[PDB]
Length: 74
Image (tube, rainbow, N blue to C red; front, side, top):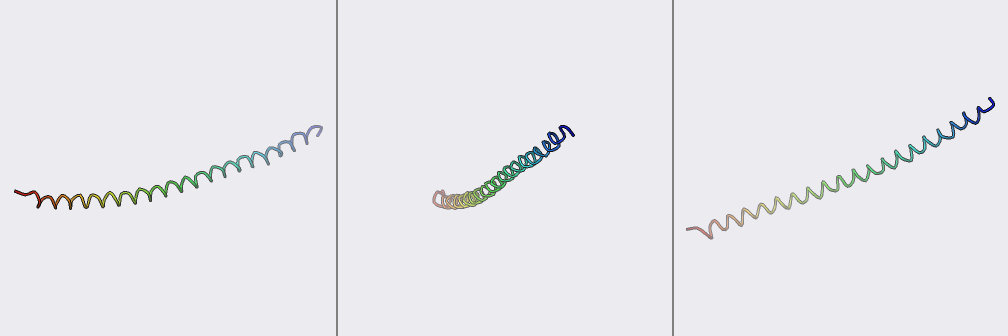
C-alpha cells in the first residue's frame, strides 16, 4: 500500500473525467442531431410548398395551351 492511493485514487480521478468528457461530448453530439433533424424537416416543408406551386403552374400551362387551341385553328 506504499503507492496504492497514488494509483487507485488516481484511476478514480480520470473515471470522473472520462465519464464526464464522453458525456459533455455525447450531449454536444445529440444537440447537433437535434438541430439537424430540425433543418431536415423545415426543408421538407420548403419542398412540399414549392412542388404545390410547380403543380399549380403546370395547370395554367395546359389552360393557356387549350386557349390557344381555339385562338389558332384553321
